[PDB]
Length: 284
Ligand SMILES: O=C1NCN(c2ccccc2)C12CCNCC2
Image (cartoon, rainbow, N blue to C red; front, side):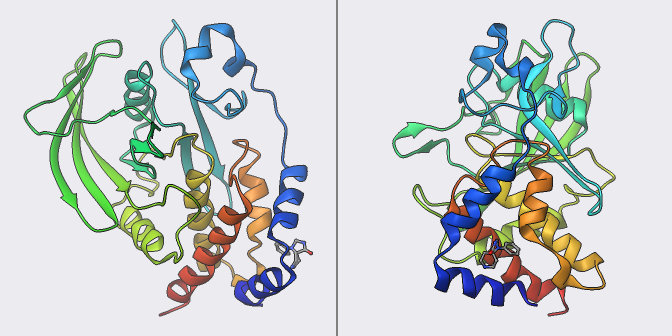
């Protein structure tokens, strides 16, 4: 059955809130003891969003190895993602330390720095070529190389330098700039165009470390991005694309980070994105 037929019954039955609540009830509960240590209170944006101990990313330092970030490892799809919060004023140096240590090629940003009149994450990359950023706590330098501004997203070329070894790497910044301040996009067309641009860059490919993906909390929009990507990859691999169960993929991803998909509207949008994206994957 085309995932869309099923989509239609849930709309007519008006059962989005119902299914969403079922996911919330069946989701994994694992300890997050490191996130809750008193020394880490200013490293968390939200008191109720923490990485599990078993899947957290560790910083390579003896002082304090903690960052609010999780490794999502999808065994059948052969994809890995790091999902993290938007960086705070005192964790911008930790953020770039993680990108360096994990060998990531790409950063995917799904929020604006200001939304709803409030700050949703630090200004953590340079806005002008000639004004580079230095992170003294982690010994990194970050330079803006080029910027390509389009109607629905911006792509930036960044140079990250490990000041300790003088090694450099090219990082690509994929910034989706048009998610609305309230609700979800009316059409998934621009979100799917954006996902295909990240894939075309090589950022999601096994020759690199995992992509780093964030929004403000790193669970809602960030969850929608990895759920859509993995479901479309599984539809490309399986003899029967109709066997891909989006609810079962989401519960597998929730073994690695709590709270992925924050609302019934984000769940419906994820279904729409996968249904509309499949009309490319299956030969069009
Ligand atoms: O009864 C249900 N429980 C959940 N869900 C569902 C979700 C993902 C894959 C298959 C089925 C439905 C059945 C179809 N429409 C109503 C809600």
